[PDB]
Amino acid sequence: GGPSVFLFPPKPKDTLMISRTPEVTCVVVDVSHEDPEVKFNWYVDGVEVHNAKTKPREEQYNSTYRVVSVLTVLHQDWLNGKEYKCKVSNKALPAPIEKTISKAKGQPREPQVYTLPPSRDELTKNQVSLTCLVKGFYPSDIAVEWESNGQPENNYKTTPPVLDSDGSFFLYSKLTVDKSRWQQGNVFSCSVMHEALHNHYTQKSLDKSTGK
Amino acid sequence: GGPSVFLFPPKPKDTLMISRTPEVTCVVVDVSHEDPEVKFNWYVDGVEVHNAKTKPREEQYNSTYRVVSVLTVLHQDWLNGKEYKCKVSNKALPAPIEKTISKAKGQPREPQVYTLPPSRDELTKNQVSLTCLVKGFYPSDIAVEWESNGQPENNYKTTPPVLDSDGSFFLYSKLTVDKSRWQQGNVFSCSVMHEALHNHYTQKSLDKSTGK
Amino acid sequence: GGPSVFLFPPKPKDTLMISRTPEVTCVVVDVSHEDPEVKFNWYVDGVEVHNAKTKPREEQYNSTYRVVSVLTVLHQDWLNGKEYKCKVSNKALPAPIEKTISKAKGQPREPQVYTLPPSRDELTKNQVSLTCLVKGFYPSDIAVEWESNGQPENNYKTTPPVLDSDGSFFLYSKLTVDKSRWQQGNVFSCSVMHEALHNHYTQKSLDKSTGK
Image 1 (cartoon, one colour):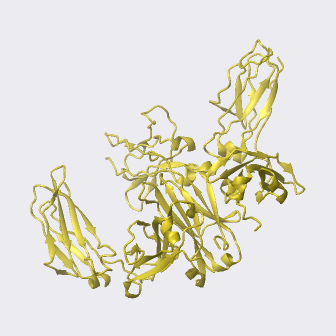
Image 2 (image 1 turned 90 degrees about the vertical axis):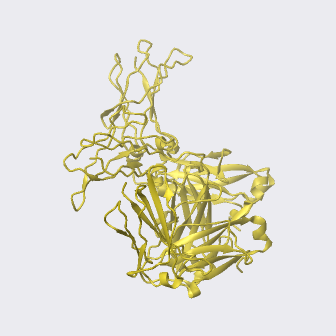
Image 3 (image 1 turned 180 degrees about the horizontal axis):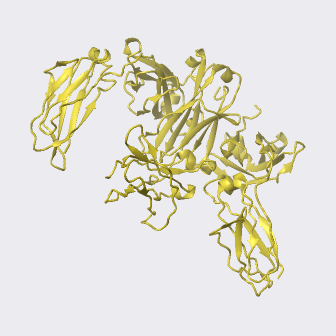
């Protein structure tokens, strides 16, 4: 009944790491009640692809459906930039809607990662802010995390990728740790994951000796 | 006639990296010439599917044919220790044989990675050697590499994993660089890939000011 | 059925240290239990030596015997590159099996021994690891041992000799000692025994002595 499709690219984390599988999603919006199940066929460069299960007729509080179709997309295909259309092949609908999705085209650029210690004014406050400047990467598909002593840190917020003057992107990651951990020799490292990096991974540490 | 059978596990780098596809190898020597094709049907728990990447046979300089069968092993599937579609069952051989292969079982341990600067006795030499001690990992499947800035450094040799006194393993990676690069302040990082590490990856840097 | 013969080379310490005895040992396995006839013709440079030590054979689970023959030779004979053929004559195998045992020929390279202190990240743990890098020796037959005050520090593991890029071999020795012993001011030395060294022996000390 004249639906709307929302595209969803895979997470760069899931794309660039092996422990989490990547998925590509085409969320349908406001489909008719006479067709509660929407048949979804994944057209990988026009080639029909099997499996790729879908969420079975999930319904909002309003009289509408939020049918979600996912596909276990391999990492190498998304790295090489395979276009996925998600053609709607429902039984009784109007003309099909094609919405291709793929990796961001263009020459990949290796990000330059810089760890910035907190300002001296931040040492007045209880919690200091640790800054990871990731700049120079052209594809915005990046994953920036933090870790200390080999274990992940979850008290971080990362800005969205901001387009630079060079045509590349930059962002910042702010890890908020309390002053007690920072004033002792605790090593905090931001680990970014980008397709243009060597081994799709790099790490920059920050352990209060940066700038000494 | 049943030939001799040899099994090769997938490389630890390819298992924990996006850009490399893991593959099991079942190179079999002295295969009979009169029956070239070998059956390659072996599920994890029997025979259920037909997914196998058939490869052409390799011929030795005399009359000892060899068959090579490799298949693309999923990264998540190998980390749990499953069997794959690689068996040896010749048409001439009446009794097929099943050579099992799986990832080593046991509790994984996270390796502790230490970068050691060259000894002061090595500063007289033209080339200094940087050592990456990786110790405390129970699965010996690990890939240790070196890099400077962002580009990899290929002038490294890595020892095989050595069983420690506590049941875990350790090894070393010796990166041989020129003494001029060491005194110039270049930063070299050894990057190891183990399944028990966070993000299956860690990176320890090394420069002339490490530890004074 | 068919007898399989494995030659055992002398231990690298026992052939380079006087307190021990070289063990040119021949172990023939999978010989028939119904054949109590063996020969001990040790063709040392084409000359049979009567100093071979015959022992009662070892019985396996199946009907087979494991005859072990140990021949003791002087240290200077093995280091001069002599052949130690052992003629194994028995009624099970009509062809006598000769095992060519000799020192690995080639120009000997003197190993360069470097002691590396524990990394500053290692000092957090209660047990630090002390490293002896032995590199640049061509004959892989080497012996590395640790000591502190003239007494053997037996809590060490040594990697196998890894072939270097220039044709020589290298390895590492890791001595695990308590953090209290390291920071007290104790001196530890790795003792390396190689045939290309002066007096077939060298050692490098390692103590808590920060440079400059």
